[PDB]
Length: 49
Length: 49
Image 1 (tube, chains in turn blue, cyan):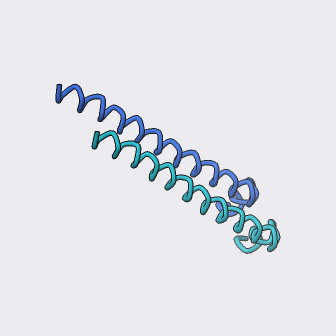
Image 2 (cartoon, each protein chain N blue to C red):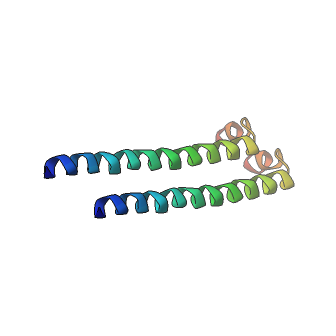
């Protein structure tokens, strides 16, 4: 019973974990895309040029 | 009961966390875009030139 309850509990906390991590990954990627498009996609290539 | 209440509670605090972080990411990206467009998109390339 304890391994079972701990199993479903950990399953919940873990799916919640990958969920929130996926969310922060989403806002991060979206923010970075909005910034890089705000700056100019070819301008950074000039910066590395 | 305690793992459950802690689970929904942490889920709330975490979704709130990624929410506020997404908000600060939004005001940050918007502010940076407004500044970089205020300055001139090609001017920075000249600065790196």
